[PDB]
Length: 10
Length: 9
Length: 229
Length: 233
Image (cartoon, rainbow over all chains, first blue to last red; front, top):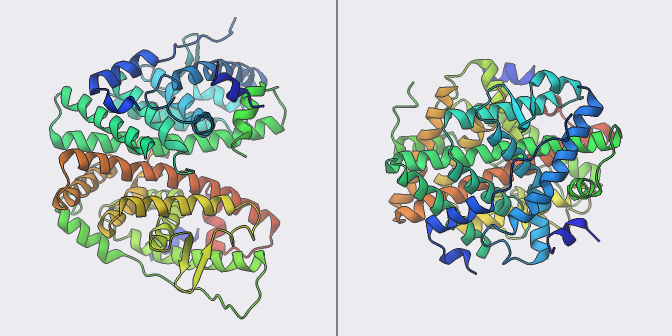
């Protein structure tokens, strides 16, 4: 659930 | 130190 | 892809336009205030860095997993190159933000940081001696993104070649002879080995500070740091 | 000095002639090995390679022109990077393995036998793969190695070192032109070679952390010179 995984998507 | 002596040898 | 069919001026135009802004510190020193200011800034720059990276040509063409890996590998090198770039016109000083200029004397404050401050200041001075330009800078930082984790893996190495082609195009545009062009290309890329070194020493001091729990770290910074061990 | 007046081809001859030898291990397949003693073989090999490296450095154009203090500093910074690029060089024609010695070839599934170091193994294999990918040449390799020597510790101190580095870039380009590459292929390859040094620097920094860990456990034999080299970090 890495933050980076989310932020690269947003 | 050891390197010092190896270098100037 | 798409990055490969851009011209050299378009590639530099893209990278100039992707550039993140210079952020200000939440500033209104010791180990706790130093580290609290710096990690807050780092956290803020990281979010901009992530959106910069998606604007680097060739980057979005990779899988999300490859993008994560390259950013986890290189994020500190990228923050460092930015710091050293900002700091060029301010000799003996590091411009963490326009309202946060720090001497090496304040590096003493934190345990083990003065060594990294001195290496950063050297890099900055070196950039100054070489009269590094903005166009060249953005190429170097893109190179760091694509290159730093690239071995733990063609399109990406073709993208790196495109950026080499771009740097050379900038130096030729600026008037350099062919020999000045390859010598300067060499000087620039060698600096990336020292930026790597600084990042590894900084990451080790970051983990050490994580452990000494002097300052709480953001979850993002913790995960960026964790990815290195 | 005499280094600045060398021609490209003289530079290449100089460096090739200074090449240290490949040494053998005391590895014996008949003997059982623990991860400890397997590591002792590698540190023992590194220690002997180091003595050769120190005398090879003396023959790198421009190195002897430096003060003793600066030679010391440059070698202390670069020693592991140099051992590592040599190992990767030796391993080029053995995909999936590291040729520490002619009688000591380890694939990466043997590199798990030691904890926290299979990743270092992987990075070396990744690097030897890259050399193979590019078909790195012996003459490029010796240029690269001398670059590490002069460059690694240069921004932790001099205009002389930078003039010599420029000579080596010139030599690299000459080698590529004479191999018939276009100007565009030459600058691209130049960049490809120099970007390797960033990876070699990373591996050294990471190996140095494993070296320090190894010493703290006082399980694996480290020699007095290795201990002092490590300490310099």
